[PDB]
Amino acid sequence: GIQRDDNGRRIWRRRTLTKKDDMLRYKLQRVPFVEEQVRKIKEVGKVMTMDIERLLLSEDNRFEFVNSVAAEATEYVEKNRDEYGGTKKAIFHVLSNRVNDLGFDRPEAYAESDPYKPGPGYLKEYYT
Amino acid sequence: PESFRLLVRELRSLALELNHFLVSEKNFQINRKEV
Amino acid sequence: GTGFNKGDILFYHREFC
Amino acid sequence: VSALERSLRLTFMDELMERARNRDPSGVSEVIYDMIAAGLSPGPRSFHGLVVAHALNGDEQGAMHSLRKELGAGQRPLPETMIALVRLSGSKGNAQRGLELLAAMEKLNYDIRQAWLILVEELVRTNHLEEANKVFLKGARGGMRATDQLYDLMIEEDCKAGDHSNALDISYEMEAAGRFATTFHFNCLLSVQATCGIP
Amino acid sequence: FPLFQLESADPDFYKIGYVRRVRAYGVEFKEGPDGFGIYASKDIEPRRRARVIMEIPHELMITIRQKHPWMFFPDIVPIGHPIFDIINSTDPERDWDLRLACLLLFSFDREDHFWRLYGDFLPAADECSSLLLATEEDLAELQDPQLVSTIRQQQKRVLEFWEKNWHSGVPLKIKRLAEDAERFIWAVSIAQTRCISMKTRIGALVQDLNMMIPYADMLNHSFEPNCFLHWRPKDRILEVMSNAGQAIKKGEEMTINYMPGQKNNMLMERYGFSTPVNPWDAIPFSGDSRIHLNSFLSVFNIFGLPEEYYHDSELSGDDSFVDGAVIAAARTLPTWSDIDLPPIPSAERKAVKELQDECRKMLAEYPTTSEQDQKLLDSLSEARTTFATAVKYRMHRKMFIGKIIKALDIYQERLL
Amino acid sequence: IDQLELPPRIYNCLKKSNIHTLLDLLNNSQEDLIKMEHFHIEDVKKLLDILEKK
Ligand SMILES: Nc1ncnc2c1ncn2[C@@H]1O[C@H](CSCC[C@H](N)C(=O)O)[C@@H](O)[C@H]1O
């Protein structure tokens, strides 16, 4: 097992696949043309939808999950009243905090803004 | 609630009383709710 | 649903120095 | 530390610890002044012998005064020294002093879980169940997890006294900590629920 | 300005799991002369809750029920296969490792099974540290007759099972699993050293399982782990979670507690390794001389109840001395306690001296010392893995007894 | 970078990589410049010296 040659450096057998996995070729690839789709997914708020499903996989009962989130949200508003109700929503803050607690990274309260707004007074108009 | 408080009065017109009691799970004391 | 199952010593006792 | 200093400390601490165990707070005071005369500085373990000697003779005021001497000398009391004072406070039913000392241990950055357990059993043993419940709930609601033996002690003693409100509060905290109630604990609550006239 | 300013495992090791939904977060698999390990590839910052380190899908595991009847999750053994009869003929209590070994060898024979690929990263017969692979000369270096007899019984039990079930008349689909006894012994060694037992819920069925879990059997053991395993029933994923609130530095090894409360001889019998800082290791004292338990704990800042002893590392600053060995010393030394009675220093010195003499009497039972064993390991060039494991075991026990003599010396002086 | 006295081989490499200004060159590390073809380690010191002298 333990082998040292001449100069005291231990020499050892590096473990390798030494076998063929056909799943390696056809699965570690990528589609190149989803930039528009990715940007709309974030725009419509679909990312938090996946995060909610992620959090519910760690929960035994979805009704106690709902109650716990509301309880945590109530605590945020009492602690800092003026920071919530506009661009930052307390329930959205709770959900993003709970995703970050798992070690993943999300923007605070999923809040994002349009960088191409042509100054104050201008509202983006939605094409139904 | 106004829907239930109004119901109690209409039942009182028929000589029936409808009391709501809360039994404490801690000390078992009965509280009559103001209806 | 969500309604189921009810939803100072050591102060003023320091070294004079 | 020289060899001469170590030799004197051994014989000074031999005499001091032989009078603390003799339940003689007065003698433990004489040796400390002997140490001061010799120039030796009384450390945390010399004032521990003074606290213990007073504590063993049921003397809460002298033991508290000894702790003030230790703090006034700039020494840091040992975790065992605080536990001796906390256990003494419970034996006299002084829950306020016992809670004040627990706050000091947190300030001294010690671990108050063991001293909190000792405080609660002393109050229960000395028939201060009402005070014991106040101290136990504060620790349990504060996040500390009690021992399984103390959980079974608090629930049973409250239910023997007809105190369902405290026994139900504790059993809720026992499960929140992570210890699920068994048939024994339920039988304690039922012993009181069966006499309330509401089946 | 930016212009003016342990080898990584085979890349295919993670990839074969990754294409089958294995996820690792902030960790990397690194290989060294002593084997694989999992290390933080970056600074893992503390959070309010436990962070997900690894996710392993259930379908990549080999699991069997701990308790009779033997059901496999996922069920890979066909109905009527002769391997089930071999698994079913085992002792329900003692032969859990034989049952897992049969499943493991059967899995290597399946073309679609993941462990056909994952098996190439398992230690070979000359690289596994299990004492089932140890020769009689390797057991001679243990210097522990009780452990040696335990291993010999294990080797006898494993061999007799192979001879009974892999005789000449068995079908070819059975013969090709374990063509030789050493192949079956190796499988049992893999089963013992890598099996993870947990209580899981699968669907609506809650049961205890013995599990072979890839990429989580690469976590090394620590009695102060920074990670723990968590079964996620909803999607059938084993989670490796770092401790909540614990900061993990880049390059730090990720560890779990294989066997809480177990001594080094138990770690040697099961996993073929020992630790010098095992907080549960015991030493046989006469009990004639006793020290003050409360003083010893406070001198070294050991807090908590006896079953949860821990070192308040923030109350010592830089005292590297206190570790699991001193905690083990607190549990194994003869102690007295009288509520709040203080100890007389002169009477405690006599006990400390007598305890140190008894500690040196035990070190004198060993023909060599712990330094001479340490340099023997450095001088090795053609030693079996189990030989070095046997030497590390006896050296760790010597290092433990030596730590007790050092701790008693510190305690005796700090009692002034 | 046109106004630094860089050798023509170095200049063509930086322009090929769309490094135009002094600030663009600074933000590039020493490993990235080696990644560029025809620009090697022997060229770092002479380029650093020109920026050292500047
Ligand atoms: N703390 C530790 N000290 C020494 N060896 C350890 C160890 N923790 C785990 N091991 C080794 O790792 C084995 C468990 S499997 C853990 C990963 C292993 N190195 C592998 O290649 O798969 C044990 O047999 C033991 O030999």
Image: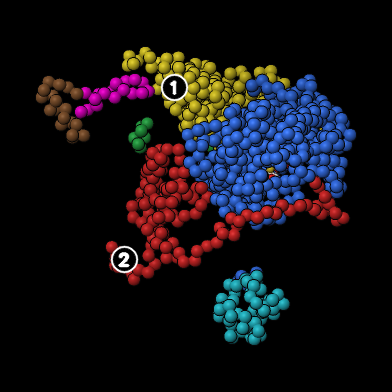
Number of callouts: 2
The percent position of residue A53, horizontal first and vertical second, equals: 43, 47
* Circle 1 residue: D167
Chain identifier, green in the render: C
Q: Give the left or right position of residue E159, taking residue E2 as reference.
A: right
The colour with which the image depicts chain D is yellow
* Magenta span main SS: loop
Q: Name the colour assigned to chain A in the rendering.
A: red
Mark 2 — on which chain does it sit?
Answer: A
Can see residue D24?
A: no
Query: Which residue is found at the position 15% from the left and 21% from the top?
Result: B16
Residue at 30% across, 68% down: A122
Q: Nearer the viewer, residue F34 or E99?
A: E99
Q: Provide the secondary structure element on which disc 1 rests.
A: helix
Identify the residue at image location x=68%, y=22%.
Answer: E337
Asked which secondary structure carries label 2, the reply is: loop
Instruction: Give the letter of the blue chain.
Output: E
* Residue at x-position 34% and y-position 71%: A118
| Residue B22 falls inside the magenta stretch | yes
Give whichever of A62, A66 is nearer the camera: A62
Residues indicated by labels 1 and 2 sit on the same polypeptide chain: no
In the rendered image, which residue does mark 2 sit on? A124
Q: Colour of chain F?
A: cyan
Distance from Cα at disc 1 to Cα at disc 2:
60 Å
Asked if the stretch drawn in magenta spans residue D72, the answer is no
Magenta-highlighted residues:
B19-35
- Of the chain colours in the picture, the one used for chain B is brown
Q: Amino acid at mark 1?
A: Ala
Quadrant (top left, top right, bottom left, bottom right) of the C terminus of chain E: top right
User: Which quarter shows the N terminus of chain E?
Assistant: bottom right
Give x and y (percent) for residue D92.
53, 19
Q: Residues within 10 Å of mark 2 (few under 14, many from 20)?
A: few
